[PDB]
Image 1 (cartoon, helix red, strand yellow):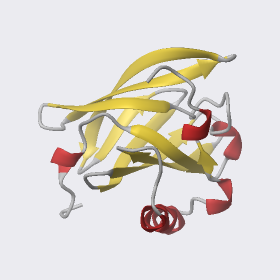
Image 2 (cartoon, helix red, strand yellow):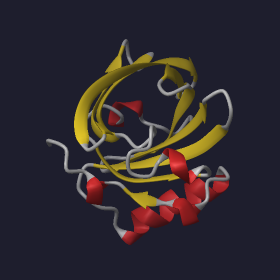
Image 3 (cartoon, helix red, strand yellow):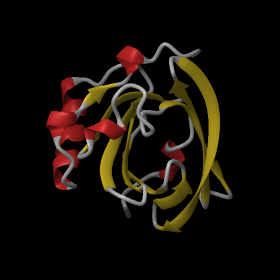
Image 4 (cartoon, rainbow, N blue to C red):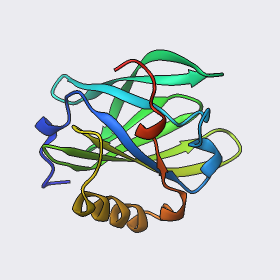
Length: 153
């Protein structure tokens, strides 16, 4: 956390990958399959504003959610249950979140791999997969989200 440069968080991100222990949450049409478009910091990252698409029965819905800082770069937001969202890696070209979602029945551990481009290089994917494993998120459950992101750019 001490090494994170939060100035790299804001910007126009695309989601490339997601991974979760409960795969059903992140498959097409799943509640936590969210097509990022933009993140902005509020009050020097005391809150995050996140704008993304959610598909409902094939139709793209533009949403904006605000997450509030708990501690460090761990944020809380309500969206299909209660979430913590932690920025666990960020660079000029790549951002990785770690999310714990609780829906009243299950806890889902997941990550999202965002890029400034449309893909991760093998080095970037290696980092993403290592971050997943460190947090008990199975790489077997990785979904490539950009390949189904037919929502408006």
